[PDB]
Image (cartoon, coloured by chain):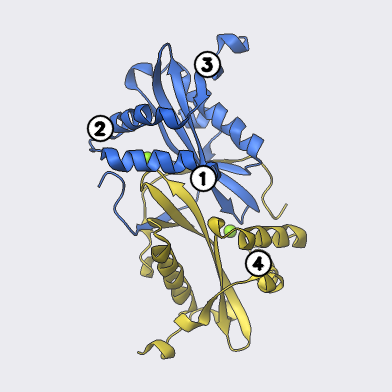
Chain colours: A yellow, B blue
Amino acid sequence: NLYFQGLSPQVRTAHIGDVPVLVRLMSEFYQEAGFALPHDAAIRAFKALLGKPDLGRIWLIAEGTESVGYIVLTLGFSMEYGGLRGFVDDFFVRPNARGKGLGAAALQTVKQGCCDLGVRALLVETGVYSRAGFEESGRMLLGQALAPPIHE
Amino acid sequence: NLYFQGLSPQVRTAHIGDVPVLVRLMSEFYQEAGFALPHDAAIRAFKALLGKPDLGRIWLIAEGTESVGYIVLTLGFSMEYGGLRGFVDDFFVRPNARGKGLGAAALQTVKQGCCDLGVRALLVETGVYSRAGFEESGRMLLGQALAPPIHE
Ligand SMILES: [Mg+2]
Ligand SMILES: [Mg+2]
């Protein structure tokens, strides 16, 4: 199939004016998991990231006249690669918009963005991912919170 | 035991002049794993990180007149926390200097550094970690390389 027939044009860069829609989408994403998302905290986070491109990038996933999803890339240095690595830090497609290939398109867009930026690797914390070239790393992830998460 | 009797003063911030020692230590770290580390790539990586504090921080672990280890903190945005999270990105103590509590001191220093910076969480990819408050996150990590790692 040809480019215009596919879903790549449906994934677009997000701007400051998109914050209200991004907040709604993140709120839906959180509600689906049974969490309440404070609107101030969400606004703060999206504005912080949009205000400093060095931190990463956000794309919205469009269908008709609506954004029906979004994906967030965050960036950090990696000694293993001697350069930046990226994370698919958050990724949401509305339930009604799933199973249409939008998620796959979003991941391809982020991967292309990474290559364009000279990003050396792309990771995600967790089907759609496997087909996008994400495979299990085999590394045990440890952590500790130093502050409450955003939904608190 | 009192502060001066402990190992916290043994963990110090690294500067540009430390690059030759950092490269040797990273080379030892890599050789222990059976890898050869290109010296140009190592120099490039340490200089990049030391040149841009927004990317993270490096500490050296001192014993007598020698650095016997180092630890690297890298920083990235996290939507989950609505702020920066940190990674213990690399961590090496020379074999002869292990089992003396130096690793524990290094991790405490990084954790304090994170709190001072308003970093919201601290993660590590993988005993010493457990006692430093790192516990299994339960999240499967997926990834794909977009470029060769530093030892290639
Ligand atoms: Mg999340
Ligand atoms: Mg490493």
Task: Look at label 3 and name its amino acid.
Answer: Leu
Marks 3 and 1 on same chain: yes
Quarter of the figure with residue B29: top left
Q: Position of residue A6 (x, y in %)?
A: 42, 86
Label 4: which secondary element: helix
Q: For the residues carrying marks 3 and 4, which lies nearer the camera in this image?
A: 3
Residue situated furthest front in the rendering: B17
The answer for how far apart the CA atoms under marks 2 and 4 are is 45 Å
Residue marked by disc 1 = B55
Label 2–label 3 contact, CB within 8 A: no
Q: Nearer the viewer, mark 2 or mark 4?
A: 2
Q: Are marks 1 and 4 in contact (CB under 8 Å)?
A: no
Q: CA distance from mark 3 to mark 1?
A: 26 Å
Q: Which mark is residue B36?
A: none
| Location of ligand 1 given as a quarter of the image | bottom right
Find disc 2 in the rendering and name its residue: B31
- Kindly report the distance in space between the C-alpha atoms of the residues bearing marks 3 and 4: 44 Å
Sequence-first disc among 2 and 3 = 3
Contact, mark 3 vs mark 4 (Cβ under 8 Å) = no
Q: Label 3 belongs to which residue?
A: B7
Residue at left 48%, top 41%?
A: B51
Please indicate whether residue A67 sits to the left or right of residue B97 in the image.
Answer: right
Instruction: Please tell me which residue is depicted at 43% across the width and 52% down the height of the picture.
Output: A84
> Marks 1 and 2: which is nearer the front?
1
**Residue A140 at what x, y percent from top left?**
42, 44
Q: Chain of mark 3?
A: B
Label 1: few (<14), some (14–19) or many (≥20) C-alpha neighbours in 10 Å: many
Q: SS for tag 2?
A: helix
Name the amino acid, label 4.
Met
Residue B55 visible in rendering: yes
Quadrant the N terminus of chain B occupies = top right
